[PDB]
Image: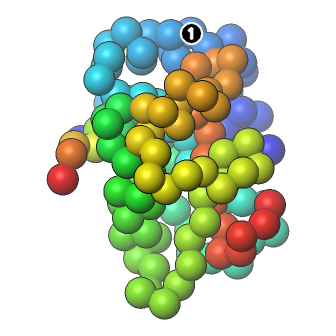
Amino acid sequence: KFVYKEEHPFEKRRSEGEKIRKKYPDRVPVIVEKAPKARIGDLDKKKYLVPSDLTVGQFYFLIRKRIHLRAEDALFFFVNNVIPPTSATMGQLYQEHHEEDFFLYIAYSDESVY
Amino acid sequence: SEVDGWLIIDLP
């Protein structure tokens, strides 16, 4: 579903994910791409090393600013097709939903579905 | 702040 998985083989992702979790023990690797069939501004950077104690709402705000969204525009995250709890931290979100390559994948959209 | 394409984010 993510173009990052298609352009990077799983073996390279899993190896780098293992190394990143060793080099940055207080951070978690996150890949953020626009959800398919979404109508919202583009995100420039997709690879994020965010602290394990950063909340989802703070990461929400960071991605909002990079897309340059207006105050009236919506931004929903999807982790494995589910909107994550906003009060949770990125470490909790990572420790529960990280894929086999040790990367956390988050899709964003203007709508609250898919 | 990037290392081979990874953005380093600090706590606000």
Residue A36, horizontal then vertical, whole percent = 78, 61
Identify the residue at horizontal 72%, vertical 51% (top origin): A82
Q: Residue B11 vs residue A10: left or right?
A: left
- Can I make out residue B9 in this image? yes
Tell me where residue A68 appears, x and y as whole percent: 41, 76
* Residue positioned 66% across, 56% down in the render: A83
Q: Amino acid at mark 1?
A: Ser
Q: Residue furthest bottom?
A: A72
Q: Is residue B9 above or below residue A21?
A: below
Label 1 element class: helix
Residue A6's x, y, as percent?
Answer: 76, 34
The answer to whether A82 is drawn above or below residue A60 in the figure is above
How many labels, in total?
A: 1
Residue A44 visible: no
> Which chain letter matches label 1?
A
Image coordinates for residue A41, horizontal then vertical, percent: 57, 75
Name the side, left or right, on which A112 lies relative to A26: right
Residue linked to disc 1: A15
Q: Quadrant of residue A66?
A: bottom left
Residue ID at (45%, 79%): A69
Kindly identify the residue that appears in the image at 80 percent across and 44 percent down.
A1
Q: Nearer the viewer, residue A58 or A108?
A: A58
